Image (cartoon, rainbow over the protein chains, first blue to last red):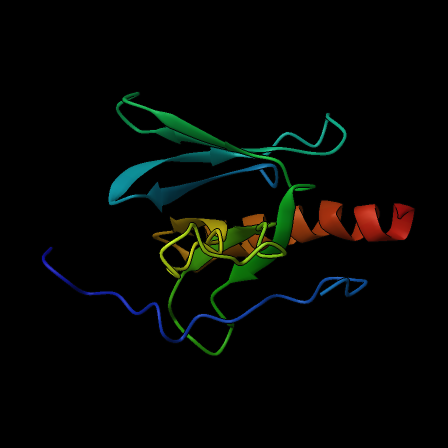
Amino acid sequence: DLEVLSEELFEDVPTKSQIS
Amino acid sequence: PSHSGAAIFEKVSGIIAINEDVSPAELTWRSTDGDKVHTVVLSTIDKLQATPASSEKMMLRLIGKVDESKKRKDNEGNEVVPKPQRHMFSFNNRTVMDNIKMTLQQIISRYKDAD
């Protein structure tokens, strides 16, 4: 366990309304 | 079950347990050993982030509303612009995240639906 991830393929889940 | 699921917070492995009995709801990641816990206000959560279904990666996160509206200097022409705070949680099972990612959203939608 030294480095086996991927924070580059993360996405955003669908959520009603969009106050961005 | 749906209001609970274990995840990784800051390289640590704990338990993420959602509290839908509140208003706004609330998330709570507690270490497995009981060294620390992180609470989340799904309301304050600017948005909900979670690994896609196409990606075997099992991880969920909640972004926090930032005060970037300021974005200014201090005096030496530097740059402050307060950075955003997001709660990242790495799950060791797409089942947990699948049961969690739905919970948060299940509630979130109620904030907009109730908005």
